[PDB]
Image (cartoon, coloured by chain):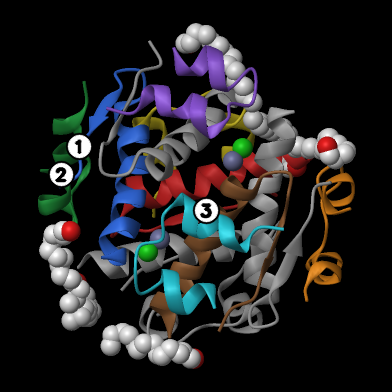
Chain colours: B blue, C brown, E red, G orange, H purple, I yellow, J cyan, L green
Amino acid sequence: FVNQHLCGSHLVEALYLVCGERGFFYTPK
Amino acid sequence: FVNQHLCGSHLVEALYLVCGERGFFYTPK
Amino acid sequence: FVNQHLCGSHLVEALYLVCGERGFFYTPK
Amino acid sequence: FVNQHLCGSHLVEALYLVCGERGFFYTPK
Amino acid sequence: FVNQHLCGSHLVEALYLVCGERGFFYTPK
Amino acid sequence: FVNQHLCGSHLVEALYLVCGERGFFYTPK
Amino acid sequence: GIVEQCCTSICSLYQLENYCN
Amino acid sequence: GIVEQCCTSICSLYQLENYCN
Amino acid sequence: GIVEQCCTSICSLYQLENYCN
Amino acid sequence: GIVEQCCTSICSLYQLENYCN
Amino acid sequence: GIVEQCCTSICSLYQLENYCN
Amino acid sequence: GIVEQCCTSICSLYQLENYCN
Ligand SMILES: *C(=O)CCCCCCCCCCCCC
Ligand SMILES: *C(=O)CCCCCCCCCCCCC
Ligand SMILES: *C(=O)CCCCCCCCCCCCC
Ligand SMILES: *CCCCCCCC[C@H](*)CCCCC(*)=O
Ligand SMILES: *CCCCCCCC[C@H](*)CCCCC(*)=O
Ligand SMILES: *CCCCCCCC[C@H](*)CCCCC(*)=O
Ligand SMILES: [Cl-]
Ligand SMILES: [Cl-]
Ligand SMILES: [Zn+2]
Ligand SMILES: [Zn+2]
């Protein structure tokens, strides 16, 4: 799904700004 | 230090494209 | 000065996520 | 609406590049 | 089409990261 | 050199908005 | 607002100028 | 995961905190 | 073009290489 | 201004919230 | 090149339009 | 770390793939 890929692209940058020093994990599957 | 914050903002997007369905763990310095 | 232009480009996106429905007024230097 | 949020994310960066020194205002509601 | 414009926005940055020194060409029409 | 890579990443997005349907040829240094 | 205008339809750069300060 | 949660519906920043390390 | 190819379906990085200079 | 303060020092969420409406 | 000119000096809309097709 | 290596030197696709799951 292309639109799912687009939202995940915005999810990653949102997580990076929110978490910061702690870091984050992204796992679609 | 802001320029590292900007560089990390581009790194996570690059990791998102490279990894895809695998996912990643972002751990900054 | 370009690096400020890049920093401002990241600032507006950060403001967009933080403010949400409130909105914001971006006034550069 | 998530897709509305995505377009607003691209609206902010488009406004920043177009306006420049004048600045801009974003107000969804 | 707005959603077509959004995908092209992500296509350009994906091409830039993939191609690198060679460069790339984007042509919707 | 990373800061040029970041600047080029913003340049292609700026070119994408400016050109629109015309398209562009990105040839880095 | 801009959401009902420039997201349902693609806005030109001139139409984007209406939302500068 | 986060894709089924924060993409079908808009997540608050507090909900985004659930995916930090 | 790339819009009809890599936007209707997700393209691999190898398929993205077809549009480099 | 936001540029003078946040492009020299990393602004957190609570600092950036000062500039919202 | 666009990099030598626009990554050292801020290019406006009309400068960036030079590199379109 | 990824920051110490890739924010000082340009990391390619194969270097960035090292940090995937
Ligand atoms: C892996 O494929 C995840 C399994 C669930 C897929 C959900 C697809 C839709 C996700 C929502 C995207 C919203 C885009 C605005
Ligand atoms: C606040 O919610 C604004 C009221 C109108 C909502 C419009 C929602 C749809 C906006 C268009 C989004 C287009 C995305 C490509
Ligand atoms: C110029 O208009 C190209 C002709 C074909 C238009 C295709 C429009 C749809 C493109 C897919 C967009 C997918 C967004 C997730
Ligand atoms: C002087 C030019 C800008 C570079 C700043 C120095 C490099 C970053 C500091 C060292 C890295 C660790 C950051 C910790 O917070
Ligand atoms: C020398 C490293 C890059 C920093 C450039 C100097 C800081 C920006 C100039 C002062 C800010 C006002 C910009 C006005 O146009
Ligand atoms: C010292 C501050 C950062 C600027 C680095 C020097 C400018 C970029 C090098 C010259 C441009 C050509 C790059 C070739 O790979
Ligand atoms: Cl999008
Ligand atoms: Cl940057
Ligand atoms: Zn940047
Ligand atoms: Zn998007």
Letter of the chain that mark 1 sits on in the rendering:
B
Give the numbered dot on residue B27.
Answer: 1
Tell me the subunit letter for badge 2: L
The structure residue drawn at horizontal position 50% and vertical position 17%, both measured from the top left corner, is H3
Marks 2, 1 in one chain? no
Evaluate whether residue G6 shows in this view. yes
| Mark carried by residue L2 | 2
Q: Which residue is mark 3?
A: C14
Residue C11: image tag: none
* Alpha carbon distance from label 3 to label 2: 23 Å
J13, H9: nearer the viewer: J13
Give residue G6's position: percent from left, percent from top: 83, 51
**In the rendered image, which quarter is residue J17 located in?**
bottom right
- Check disc 3 and report its element: helix, strand or loop: helix
Left or right, B21 with respect to C15, comes to: left
Q: Is residue I20 above or below residue G21?
A: above
Tag nearer the camera, 3 or 2? 3
Cα separation, mark 1 vs mark 3, equals 20 Å
Q: Please, which chain is the residue tagged with disc 3 on?
A: C
